[PDB]
Figure 1 (cartoon, rainbow, N blue to C red):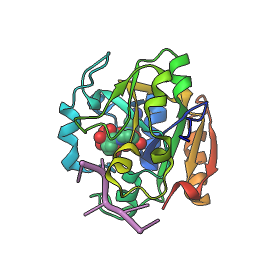
Figure 2: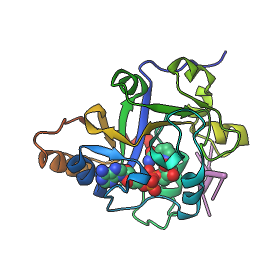
Figure 3: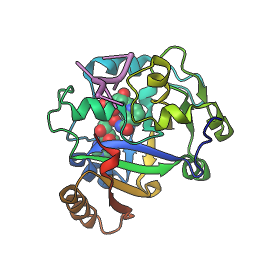
Length: 209
DNA sequence: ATGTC
Ligand SMILES: NC(=O)c1ccc[n+]([C@@H]2C[C@H](COP(=O)(O)OP(=O)(O)OC[C@H]3O[C@@H](n4cnc5c(N)ncnc54)[C@H](O)[C@@H]3O)[C@@H](O)[C@H]2O)c1
């Protein structure tokens, strides 16, 4: 019988530690189309233009790159591309943070969001704006440690939670890191912003490859 | 096993 979703429902954004100062200085994650002051790109360039044109067919609309993106799992396929040095970025997974919030925190804050049931660039992805539709997602595929096949699982593992334009830092509940050295560098950075929320910093090696 | 498609 099919796994239900966790409540609260965690959402996960991976970023390079060299971006954490910018996030704290702005007080928010910014969508790609808001030109975040990032220091490090961990993306594939060749899938960027698809996200700049992929229309979001739920209000508030626009395109995928109008939204701050999250997965419903850690240890994403995107992280595997980074871990394996397939990206232009060659720093590997160790400096990649998982920033963790929940879908309910976003709804409670009244921020406009949408979410998908699969990788968002796919033309057959479904989009939702009601948290009751989390039932439409495949929680087995989202939680799978082996995702490369079959193809439906690979697609559904990459269901996304999308928050329009910006995501306030105060909604982050945990920063998860690969190593004790990265956790210590994260706390150093949080201490430079003594008025910012300070989420717990947890080493979760099992969220990495 | 997995190099986001
Ligand atoms: N990052 C994720 O967890 C995630 C989740 C779901 C989908 N995706 C998509 C996969 C693909 C590559 O991802 P990503 O590299 O995140 O996207 P991107 O290529 O749009 O890069 C935006 C970068 O800016 C960073 N950032 C945002 N706000 C700030 C700020 N205020 N100061 C400094 N840096 C900031 C953000 O963390 C990310 O590293 C994009 O198309 C994403 O939309 C990513």
